[PDB]
Amino acid sequence: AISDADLKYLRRCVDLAREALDDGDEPFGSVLVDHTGTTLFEDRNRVKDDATAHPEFAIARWAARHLTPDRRARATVYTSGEHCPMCAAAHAWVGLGRIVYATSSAQLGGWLTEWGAQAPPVATLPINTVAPGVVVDGPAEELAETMHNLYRAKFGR
Amino acid sequence: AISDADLKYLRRCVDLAREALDDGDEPFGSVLVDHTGTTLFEDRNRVKDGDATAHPEFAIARWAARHLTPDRRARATVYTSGEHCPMCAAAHAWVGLGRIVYATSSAQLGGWLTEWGAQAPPVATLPINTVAPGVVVDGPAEELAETMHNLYRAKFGR
Ligand SMILES: C[As](C)(=O)[O-]
Ligand SMILES: C[As](C)(=O)[O-]
Ligand SMILES: [Zn+2]
Ligand SMILES: [Zn+2]
């Protein structure tokens, strides 16, 4: 279930991923939203300015520092790309709520393989393999081509 | 695959885990050792201030990314009292660290929790190589099973 409201936030994730691309980083963007609708924190990949500089992970730590457990449980995380296992686990450790993603890690994995990219050193596990209790929605068919194009800009060869 | 020298570092990890439990934190301890046998960085769990991501293996991955070249990372070993959760195993692999040696597996931990009637963590106890297929992993250490059973029971089995 991805509503029109969820798509709007996913579009903002895509914009953040493009901000990252244009700054020399990798095209991953994410947004943290309170149950009450309000955007709490937005981020993107900052690999240039540690390979662990993932925005979803920054979200998890920001949430643990700024929000009570009750507010974390009720918050939603939107993301352009489905969390890697590092980030899915961090999300569950700090007790955040629903995740909605635009493109799956399986999708990205298949595209990387087409570009002849040597396999990343972390497996593309579905969020629920890592974090079984998290409610996960995605991918968003409307945004597949756009994300393919952003990924091609960074990782195509 | 567990040498005398490896076991000595695992005993240091256990001591770090005990330090953590005595300070109010969870009993997890880890040490980063370079290819010359020199300890570079030691750490322990620090979750009690409210950040459940304050794991020592993740601190080591970030420390290593800041302080070590890619070549030095690849040749360093991470010793740990408990096998890396998926968060920490992924971070380890993303930063390009080398071998991991652990005293107790995640299979041991998960089996003990269910023995004790304790709630499972919200992160699945995936073995390191499910998350990070290329990392060389050694453990667990039979010599340390009873100690770590006792230590995890103290924190998680009440
Ligand atoms: C979707 As990611 C590589 O920022 O965990
Ligand atoms: C063995 As652990 C919970 O510090 O990743
Ligand atoms: Zn990630
Ligand atoms: Zn961990």
Image (cartoon, coloured by chain):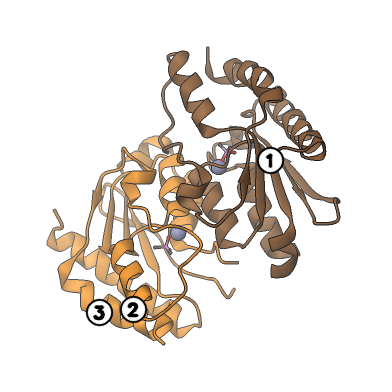
Chain colours: A orange, B brown
Mark 2 within 8 Å of ligand 1, using the beta carbon: no
Chain label for disc 3: A
Front residue of B31/B53: it is B31
Residue that label 2 marks: A114
The foreground one among B108 and A134 is: B108
Work out whether residue A63 can be spotted.
no
Identify whether B79 is placed above or below B81: below
Is the residue B47 above or below the residue A18 in the image? above
For the residue pair B133 and B148, the one nearer the viewer reads as B133
Q: Is residue B110 above or below residue A48?
A: above
> In the figure, B116 relative to B95: above or below?
above
**Hey, what amino acid is under mark 1?**
Ala
Rounded to the nearest whole Å, what is the CA distance between mark 2 and mark 3?
Answer: 17 Å
**How far apart are labels 3 and 1 at the CA level?**
48 Å
Q: Which residue is mark 3?
A: A146
In the image, which disc is placed on residue B1? 1
